Image: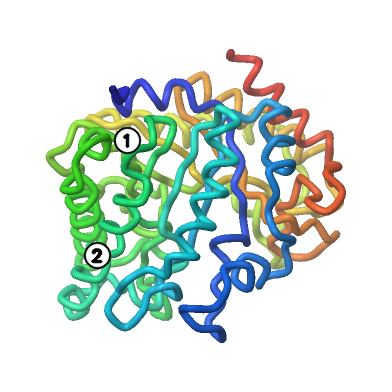
């Protein structure tokens, strides 16, 4: 039997993303090229079970395996079988370690274009893709969760990072519903498996949350990404902030997390924060304070939160979210890892 999505979310704890790995979008290869050429294409080493063991033994309860699939489809939209086999092996590392696993589609935005004009070309391909993923993983138990899309948005337009348009938010809902229908149609455990699906751009803004539509299905989870507060966590412009921990900082995060809990509850679904984190601004004390407070506040509300770990930790560079050094199996920032787990244990 499969637990309800609401039951599963209660147990997912704090999580970790295998970032810049099976999601690395490598467009100069071919659909028949070895999986390892993609997995290592953004500079990360080939994933081993020992890396997964380190994450499990630190106290994370969920791993998200972001996976980019489009480059692995042939001209008939059939997935390369060696690719599927490699994704399955990495999923198996995690499932064997008693983790919840979120398996998504990831950097598909060159072809998953949310406009009415592109709907007829996207939808059949997205449905065949999800049919094949679902079939490959049909017999997995309820620790495996599917996530339809990552940050679907109008890439390359002025609306990419501003919450979209009525049209594109509608089409994102339609793509999510089409992917879900394909998952459910494969039957077996996939009739009831929990399925995460995002708002436009996975944004937690009021506009994108409010337009989120839940299909007629009993086991849906909303997905948002919340690198919050943005100017501290992610921004490298002149607006960049490098300290965190005031009463105002805490209040602001509490109100934001309340909006996620309460908006999605009012729509009848749980919510998972599938990506969060902060970049390395030589500010570990503040990053650790934020990490602990964020996890505690989210877990008090029943919201799992999954750190984005791309194994990139270079000081004063953008997107430096790395925590586990995958080559040494030591932590780049043990204090931040410790704060994440402490925030989970504050509640559980």
In this rendered view, identify the residue nearer to me: 218 or 87.
87
* Vertical position of residue 141 compared to residue 206: above or below: above
If the image is split into quadrants, where does the N terminus sit? top left
Q: Residue at x 83, y 53 (%)?
A: 327
Q: Is residue 148 found left or right of 17 in the rendered image?
A: left
Residue under label 1, please give it: 194
Q: Which residue carries the number 2 mark?
A: 128
Which residue is more in the foreground, 295 or 106?
Answer: 106
Residue 329 x %, y %: 83, 44
Where the C terminus falls, by quadrant? top right
Instruction: Residue 98: give x, y in percent of width and height.
Output: 55, 27
Residue lying farthest to the left in this orientation: 216
The residue drawn where x is 43% and y is 65% is 81
Among the 4 quarters of the image, the one containing residue 79: bottom left
SS assignment at label 1: loop
Q: Nearer the viewer, mark 2 or mark 1?
A: 2
Q: Is residue 79 left or right of residue 210?
A: right
Residue at x 56% of width, y 40% of height: 63
Give SS at disc 2: helix
> How many residues crowd around disc 1 within 10 Å: few (fewer than 14), some, or many (20 or more)?
many
**Which of the labelled discs sits on residue 239, or is there none?**
none
Query: Which color scheme did the rendering employ for the protein?
Result: rainbow
Q: Quadrant of residue 153?
A: bottom left
């Amino acid at each position: 039997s499969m637990r309800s999505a609401s039951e599963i979310v209660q147990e997912m704890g704090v999580g970790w993303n295998l970032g810049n790995t099976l999601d690395a979008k490598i467009t100069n290869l071919s659909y028949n090229t070895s999986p390892i050429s993609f997995e290592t294409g953004w500079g990360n080493p080939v994933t081993t079970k020992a890396m997964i063991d380190k994450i499990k033994n630190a106290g994370f309860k969920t791993i998200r395996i972001p996976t980019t699939w489009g480059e692995h489809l042939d001209g008939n939209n059939k997935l390369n079988e060696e690719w599927v086999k490699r994704v399955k092996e990495v999923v198996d590392y995690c499932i064997a370690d008693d983790l919840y696993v979120i398996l998504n589609t990831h950097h598909e935005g060159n072809w998953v274009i949310p406009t009415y004009a592109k709907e007829s070309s996207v939808t059949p391909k997205l449905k065949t893709l999800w049919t094949q993923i679902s079939e490959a993983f049909k017999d997995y138990d309820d620790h495996l969760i599917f996530e339809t899309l990552n940050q679907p948005r109008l890439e390359g337009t002025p609306y990419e990072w501003t919450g979209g348009t009525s049209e594109s938010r509608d089409v994102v809902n339609k793509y999510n519903a089409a992917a879900l229908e394909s998952i459910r149609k494969t039957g077996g455990n996939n009739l009831s498996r929990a399925v995460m699906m995002p708002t436009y751009a996975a944004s937690g803004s009021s506009t994108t949350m409010n337009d989120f539509k839940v299909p007629d299905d009993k086991n849906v989870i909303a997905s948002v990404h919340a690198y919050s507060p943005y100017f501290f966590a992610m921004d490298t412009s002149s607006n960049s902030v490098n300290t965190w921990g005031s009463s105002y900082d805490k209040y602001s995060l509490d109100v934001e997390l309340d909006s996620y809990l309460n908006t999605f509850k009012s729509k009848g679904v749980p919510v998972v924060i599938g990506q969060f984190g902060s970049i390395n601004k030589n500010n570990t004390s503040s990053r650790a304070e934020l990490a602990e407070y964020y996890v505690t506040a989210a877990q008090k509300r029943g919201i799992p939160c999954v750190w984005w770990d791309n194994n990139y930790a270079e000081t004063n560079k953008g997107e430096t979210f790395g925590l586990l050094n995958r080559s040494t199996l030591n932590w780049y920032f043990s204090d931040i890892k410790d704060a994440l787990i402490r925030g989970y244990k504050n509640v559980h």
